[PDB]
Image (spheres, rainbow, N blue to C red):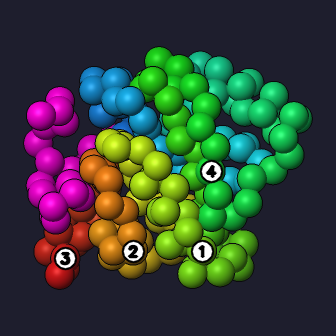
Amino acid sequence: VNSFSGYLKLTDNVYIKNADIVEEAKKVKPTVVVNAANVYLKHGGGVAGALNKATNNAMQVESDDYIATNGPLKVGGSCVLSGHNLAKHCLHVVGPNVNKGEDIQLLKSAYENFNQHEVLLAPLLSAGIFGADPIHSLRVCVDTVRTNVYLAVFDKNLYDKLVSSFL
Ligand SMILES: O=C(N[C@H]1c2ccccc2C[C@H]1C(=O)O)c1ccc(NC(=O)C2CC2)cc1
């Protein structure tokens, strides 16, 4: 039993809710919140900008030190950093950004990072300002992630479309 509330169950291990991932993280304080990161960990907008703002920019400060030491992530890769006031840990995962021309096949590799964590609160990777089709992202999630994932979808209209079209 866990503390996630109001989710629709899609499969054995994937759950979905119309929710603001920031508000959801603040209430649940999950072990892992996933950030929709880029390779530079520049958290300017979308989910990343929102999560970083909620940390009062502490996420960005920590991220800048990470990059200065380690260099950029790979598209499809991830790193574990602090969850600050939102979660124990933040798993920064880089899905391909279609608005930069990155290969959508890398979306499966991106979701594979979730399998290193037993339970996660997450957005749909490569959705929103990353330019992928969220219906496709949900399909890849379901077909790739085997651990327990609680998906937060900010837009109610999109949430309803994702549920109604789910196979
Ligand atoms: O952009 C956002 N979500 C979309 C996005 C973008 C980029 C990558 C993946 C995704 C998934 C997509 C979604 O709706 O699930 C987003 C989510 C939450 C906030 N919360 C706040 O601003 C708090 C109220 C002050 C802001 C933006």
Q: How far apart are marks 3 and 2 (CA)?
A: 12 Å
Pointer 1 with pointer 4, Cβ within 8 A: no
Q: Which amino acid does label 3 sit on?
A: Phe
Numbered mark located on residue 140 in the image: 2
The residue that appears at 58% across and 45% down in the rendered structure is 92
Q: Which amino acid does label 4 sit on?
A: Ser
Q: Distance between the residues labelled 3 and 1?
A: 22 Å
Which picture quadrant has residue 118?
A: top left
The local crowd at label 2, few if under 14, some if 14 to 19, many if 20 or more residues have their Cα within 10 Å, is many
- Name which of mark 3 and mark 1 comes first in the sequence: 1
The residue that appears at 50% across and 29% down in the rendered structure is 89
Pointer 3 with pointer 4, Cβ within 8 A: no
Numbered mark located on residue 166 in the image: 3
Comparing 156 with 60, the one in front is: 60
Pointer 3 with pointer 2, Cβ within 8 A: no
Comparing 121 with 47, the one in front is: 121
The local crowd at label 4, few if under 14, some if 14 to 19, many if 20 or more residues have their Cα within 10 Å, is many
Q: How far apart are marks 1 and 4 (CA)?
A: 12 Å
Residue extent of the magenta highlight: 1-20
Numbered mark located on residue 106 in the image: 1
Please identify, in this view, whether the residue under mark 3 or under mark 4 is nearer the observer: 4
The residue that appears at 58% across and 80% down in the rendered structure is 104
Give the residue number, with chain letter if any, for mark 4.
78
Q: Where is residue 155 in the image (x, y as percent from the top left)?
A: 31, 55
Q: Which amino acid does label 2 sit on?
A: Val
Residue 23 appears anywhere in the view = no
Q: Distance between the residues labelled 2 and 1?
A: 10 Å
Q: Position of residue 60 (x, y in %)?
A: 70, 30
Q: How far apart are marks 3 and 4 (CA)?
A: 27 Å
Q: Work out whether 63 lies above or below 129.
A: above
Please give left or right for residue 49 compared with residue 42 in the image.
left
